[PDB]
Image (cartoon, coloured by chain):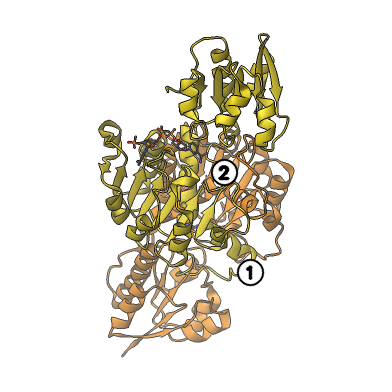
Chain colours: A orange, B yellow
Amino acid sequence: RLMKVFVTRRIPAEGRVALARAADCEVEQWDSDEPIPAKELERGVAGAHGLLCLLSDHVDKRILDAAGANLKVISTMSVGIDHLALDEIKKRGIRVGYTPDVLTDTTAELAVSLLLTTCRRLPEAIEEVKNGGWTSWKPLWLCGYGLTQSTVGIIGLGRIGQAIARRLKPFGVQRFLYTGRQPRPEEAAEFQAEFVSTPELAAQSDFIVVACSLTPATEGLCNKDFFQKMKETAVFINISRGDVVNQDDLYQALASGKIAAAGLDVTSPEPLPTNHPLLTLKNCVILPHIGSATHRTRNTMSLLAANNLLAGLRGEPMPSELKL
Amino acid sequence: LMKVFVTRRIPAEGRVALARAADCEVEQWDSDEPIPAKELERGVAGAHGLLCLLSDHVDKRILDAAGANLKVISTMSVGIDHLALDEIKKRGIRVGYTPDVLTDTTAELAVSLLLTTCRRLPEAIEEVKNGGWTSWKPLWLCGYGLTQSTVGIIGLGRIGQAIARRLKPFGVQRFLYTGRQPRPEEAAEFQAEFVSTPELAAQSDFIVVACSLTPATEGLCNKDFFQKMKETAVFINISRGDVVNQDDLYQALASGKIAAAGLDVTSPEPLPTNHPLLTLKNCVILPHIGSATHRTRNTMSLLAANNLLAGLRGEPMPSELKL
Ligand SMILES: NC(=O)C1=CN([C@@H]2O[C@H](COP(=O)(O)OP(=O)(O)OC[C@H]3O[C@@H](n4cnc5c(N)ncnc54)[C@H](OP(=O)(O)O)[C@@H]3O)[C@@H](O)[C@H]2O)C=CC1
Ligand SMILES: NC(=O)C1=CN([C@@H]2O[C@H](COP(=O)(O)OP(=O)(O)OC[C@H]3O[C@@H](n4cnc5c(N)ncnc54)[C@H](OP(=O)(O)O)[C@@H]3O)[C@@H](O)[C@H]2O)C=CC1
């Protein structure tokens, strides 16, 4: 009576071993580092009891139907959940596992890394070395934007947004602002952060860091209108989802001098075509969605995803279940 | 009128200070490019005051060029290893430099570099532009975290302290440091342990060098340093080029003896574009941009000018170097 499990990719070893040991399961896997096409996904999920997927696998009505009534648990190796058809998943009584907390510190780290390479202009500095542009120490050359006495606006002061604030505080940040559905005064206290409106966040911040979820509410949030309320000297950082940022409005505002610079960990689509105008701008840094990328973290998420699925398979509590 | 030579275009505020001085005759190297030693010797002849950069070589020949008039040298920098201090002392010439005003900015850059290096941002940046990016991937571009790490700081001075303070909320579990002498009061903020240099290499997951360049720091970071470091560790230098044995570093990185290196300084500066370290994907090199924010740089310009003026008029200087 072996439950079928499908894994949509080669995952870190700790998660792969935990599945392999599950003697009540047979594990079928997409043996590749490359994304599984949708029709190969539809083929592999057929009659699966459990699905172990990733943030870039689109788990829509099409693949839930391809799977049929066997499917009881979908374990995603990510904290983001927007790639999942939650309404349809709910309707069918299927359990969801995801990976919060476990990747928080690492992602916060990556966000501050990105904010700092962008704000201190490291990539064009690097290139001035390689291309022969460097001729000496120069007093007014490659001057960037410093965090001392600065105001930091965070859109979405969740666990990752809190961990980012905590990492920027010792940099001499004067004032923390934040935006969202409701205040979090218990959370914000640590930073003496102020709850403000989006327009006030834009007008007042030297640094804007977006660390919210993708919802209907957050889709297209940072558009022309937003970059226009921003300071000309401000730096814009997005580590959330690509669809939060209008990329045409971003390019324009970067190209026209409406903001100083931006660093993106996330894009629309992913990958961004090497062709994209964003990639031609020297005041734009784009990273390939590496927020949670250290082995230890990815090992930890992989094991968490495994254990979510196995418990979900056995009718047990999950280490980290997403409810309803 | 006291004669002044300025070896470069300095940021406005400081240049303004010098243009508003009625007691002074100011000559500038009117350029963003460094002064030939030959032009510097001509430039400084007769000068009472020299306002100079960390990259000008103020040796015997330039002091002798300048002559007995020379009363103040004011450098737009904190480092002083480009001044022949022994000769300056004995000639009784006063020195100005720029401590403190650049401490926060430089620490900021050093953590910038450590993070760009250890989270592999360059490699990442180019996987994007060169079409290597194909999806999100669980085992790809994984770097080295600060959580539960050991950071060794070589030189827990002003900047080394501002560095550790910025590193602490990243979850560092342990700070070690070394130097000539412990600094117990300053060490305490980080609970840092003073250890030898071999022990600091052996234990540290991340190594930051924020020391001054002296005869005893010179070539400190060499083959045997790199040999005792963890094969997983990351090496950052923001001090001076000459603290590092560059060949040993190249050798170490190319053979996997350490994980990677971020450098804000090299030997010589600029590093030639075909140099061996520029062929390694695990080596990040920045063009000595530690103090590069406009606001820090103007404050430096203004300091360097006021230190000069004050010396020229026999007054106490905002920041004099004690010789
Ligand atoms: N770059 C990377 O590799 C990674 C990226 N991420 C992304 O970042 C997100 C971080 O989530 P995490 O902190 O773990 O969990 P959280 O749910 O706590 O973070 C989401 C935040 O978004 C806020 N938010 C929701 N709607 C809005 C809105 N309309 N305007 C402003 N803020 C809003 C929420 O606050 P409120 O409800 O009060 O509005 C909350 O603070 C993930 O959902 C994921 O998409 C996560 C991990 C790694
Ligand atoms: N990349 C850049 O733009 C910048 C580079 N610099 C460089 O950084 C240096 C530090 O400046 P700052 O902190 O303001 O000056 P400090 O005078 O405070 O010097 C810092 C440290 O050098 C240390 N030192 C001397 N010898 C050794 C050694 N044997 N081993 C370990 N440490 C040693 C001192 O420690 P101890 O006496 O106990 O040995 C002190 O901790 C400057 O001298 C300059 O060369 C500075 C600013 C910007």
Does residue A105 appear left or right of residue A117 in this picture?
left
Q: x, y percentage for residue A190?
A: 36, 37
Residue B114 appears in view: yes
Amino acid type, callout 1: Gly
Q: Quadrant of the N terminus of chain B?
A: top right
Residue found farthest to the bottom: A1
Q: Quadrant of the C terminus of chain B?
A: top left
Please name the residue that numbered disc 1 is placed on. B131
Check the image and report above or below for A154 versus B300.
below
Amino acid type, callout 2: Cys
**Callout 2: few (<14), some (14-19), or many (20+) C-alpha neighbours within 10 Å?**
many
Q: x, y percentage for residue A121?
A: 59, 46
x 53%, y 77%: residue: A34
Does residue A174 appear left or right of residue B3 in this picture?
left
Q: x, y percentage for residue A17?
A: 32, 78
Corner quadrant of residue A233: top right
Q: x, y percentage for residue B233?
A: 38, 58
Front one among A150 and B188: B188
Decide: marks 2, 1 in contact (CB < 8 A)?
no
Does residue A300 appear left or right of residue B46 in this picture?
left
Front one among A17 and B278: B278
Residue B320 appears in view: no
